[PDB]
Amino acid sequence: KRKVVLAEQGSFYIGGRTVTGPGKFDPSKPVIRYSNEGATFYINQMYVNFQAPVRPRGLPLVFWHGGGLTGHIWESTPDGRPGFQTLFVQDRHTVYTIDQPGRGRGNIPTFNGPFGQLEEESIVNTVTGNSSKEGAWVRDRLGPAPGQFFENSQFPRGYEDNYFKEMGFSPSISSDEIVDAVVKLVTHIGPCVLVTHAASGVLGMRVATHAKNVRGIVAYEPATSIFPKGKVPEIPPLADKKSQIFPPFEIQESYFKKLAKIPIQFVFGDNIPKNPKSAYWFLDWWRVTRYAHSLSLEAINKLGGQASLLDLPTAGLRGNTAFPFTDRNNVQVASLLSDFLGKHGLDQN
Amino acid sequence: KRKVVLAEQGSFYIGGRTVTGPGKFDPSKPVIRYSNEGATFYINQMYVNFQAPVRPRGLPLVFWHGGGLTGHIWESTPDGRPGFQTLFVQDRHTVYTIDQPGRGRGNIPTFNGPFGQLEEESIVNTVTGNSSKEGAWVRDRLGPAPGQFFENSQFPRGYEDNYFKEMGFSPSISSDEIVDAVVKLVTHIGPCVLVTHAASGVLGMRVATHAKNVRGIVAYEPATSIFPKGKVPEIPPLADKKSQIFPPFEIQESYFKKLAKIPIQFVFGDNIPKNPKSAYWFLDWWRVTRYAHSLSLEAINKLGGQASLLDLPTAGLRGNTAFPFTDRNNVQVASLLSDFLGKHGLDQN
Ligand SMILES: COC(=O)c1ccccc1S(=O)(=O)NC(=O)Nc1nc(C)nc(OC)n1
Ligand SMILES: COC(=O)c1ccccc1S(=O)(=O)NC(=O)Nc1nc(C)nc(OC)n1
Ligand SMILES: COC(=O)c1ccccc1S(=O)(=O)NC(=O)Nc1nc(C)nc(OC)n1
């Protein structure tokens, strides 16, 4: 289960831009100084790792971590079992894993001065936000409240510290610049499949509308829905009658229609309530978010698309959290991803 | 050359602590708030990646990136050639690569509020520092000034964008907590060899004094020298008559003496001047820093140690920058590391 034969592996940086400070650089003066003087900074670049099997079959897969995460989530589970990177190299696909701009090995754009500030220019905000352990517990549906598990949970219990340690903040890089980096990667790779998660769901949909090389999308528990501009359907508030899900992203119809040209599957785990749940905000949020996604997929299919929603319990998999690819049954989740790739000819040369 | 066979690979988090905000978490209230209310945060943890060959021989190697870097520098060179991770798995060692706390996939400790601030506590400073491309160019001895290359340079010229994109800022995490994370890793792995670089040089020396499982150290271009407390020798200022090298780190003699029990090699590349160089601050800084290291190694050897300084040009390798393990001749640099491991039996079971 653990062995991997790689024809090659490596990593590289792609995308980003530069910004410059005032003045000029003098090599005779002391170089280590609290100064942006004469300085060029590379910002907003992305880190990319690849592992290629011997005799690859089908298209390369690009695994794109969710919000506050890194490519670690595709390498191993919190309890140390193989992640989708190993499983899909064994399945004879070349596997790319990224750390998007602002996360992990991607660039965090800060300089000499208050965080994110280059002289009088704010590149990213000095004030950050970040989830807590308690917030992530309920966001990821480990259970209804921090420290409590659903009876059926597939989470690797006992490895809570390892799991939460993988999460962190993201600086306020524009989503446009994150999408731009991945479009550039897709141009470099050629035809490929995006496998996204949570926050990267909407971003991968956007990439596909800018990059014909994206030949398929599988999105685990996408966090933000997408619709044609001016065609957002009625979406109810949450059960508290005060809160809303994330405002759906709206794109020009000419771009939205490109989503009808490739197979797209959204995958949801377990324990999303069918009925309003005012006592558990994030459970209710997932109910309405999943509903919004069902309408988004319906809109793609009304344009001639092939967009599907897979609820893992309907496939016989019970208890999955919002990270099904690191849960205890992740091999069975991977099997369902292999099935999708195979049906759509994405595992053939 | 590119093929690699792994018995297993993976990644995990280790080390760190938790800090908490005020109050209690309520799962019925909107979870996504600009608030540290009832929040627990994991901070200062380290990311660790491992790749194990089939039938390893000798001790595992722990590659520890320099300042502002990540484990990427051991994965691949800027022009995409195999890094030391691949080369040493091929050489039958299990290889660990880390992103230390504050860098890459390691934790950046920030919350809801100004960067680094958890309510009234400053976990790390809101004001950051960061090198520029121009500063790094001269720091790493690509040439005497930005845009210029030393004759016979082994830098992968043409891949400057890739190279500089791998560098970034570090938040003000205490060095004690960075050392602590690696001590914990060394306890987890067992007997091992540390391979350090620039800023991580002094940190690896510190780890060895706290961790008997460190059985050898190879340090590329270490940035800060280390001496027994009260026993720092006279070190001259730089040629500009005003600047100094980094204040040497001082440790109690009982800990310093632990450095005499293991083989230690410091490795330097090319173009460090033998004579004062007022016009090029960082070249002169390297001259005096290397001198200080020569005295540190002598101090270890006078306590019965096995410490040595390897100047790559004396071994027949010309043109190396301060990242010799990513230069064009990195295979030959790796061969010298294999030689060190073999001399001391660190490549035998
Ligand atoms: C991996 O999960 C997602 O991708 C994900 C999944 C669902 C919603 C949102 C995200 S997120 O990551 O973009 N953003 C996020 O979680 N932010 C956040 N911020 C605060 C301040 N508190 C909390 O509490 C949960 N969350
Ligand atoms: C990888 O190199 C080292 O490890 C390394 C090598 C030699 C010295 C220092 C470092 S460092 O990385 O700890 N710190 C550093 O470089 N800081 C810095 N800060 C500013 C503000 N400007 C510049 O200009 C160079 N440098
Ligand atoms: C690393 O060295 C330098 O950086 C370096 C150092 C000094 C001069 C030039 C270079 S160079 O690399 O930019 N370019 C170079 O050498 N060009 C060159 N072109 C021809 C056509 N013939 C010869 O030499 C006969 N040289």
Image: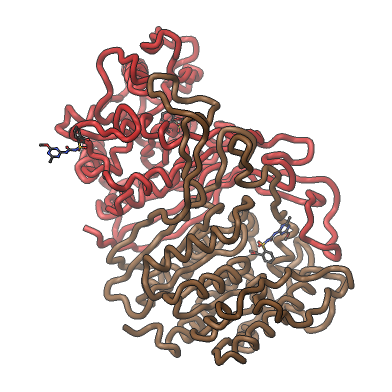
Chain colours: A brown, B red
Q: Is residue B93 left or right of residue A180?
A: left
Res. A322 image quadrant: bottom right
Image location (x, y in percent) of residue B47: 51, 50
In this rendered view, identify the residue nearer to me: B193 or A50.
Answer: A50
In the rendered view, tell whether residue B110 sits above or below residue A71: above
Instruction: Answer whether residue A14 is visible to the viewer in this image.
Output: yes
What residue sits 84% from the left and 76% below the top?
A277
In this rendered view, identify the residue nearer to me: A33 or A342.
Answer: A33
Instruction: Answer whether residue B219 is visible to the viewer in this image.
Output: no
Q: Residue at the right extreme?
A: A241
Quadrant (top left/top right/bottom left/bottom right) for the N terminus of chain B:
bottom left
* Number of numbered discs: 0
Quadrant containing ligand 3 reads top left
Res. B214 image quadrant: top left
Image location (x, y in percent) of residue B27: 83, 63
In this rendered view, identify the residue nearer to me: A91 or A241.
Answer: A241
What residue sits 62% from the left and 66% below the top?
A199
In the rendered view, tell whether residue A101 sits above or below residue A192: above
In the rendered view, tell whether residue A125 sits above or below residue A206: above
What residue sits 76% from the left and 45% below the top?
B20
Image location (x, y in percent) of residue A283: 77, 73
Image location (x, y in percent) of residue A194: 48, 73
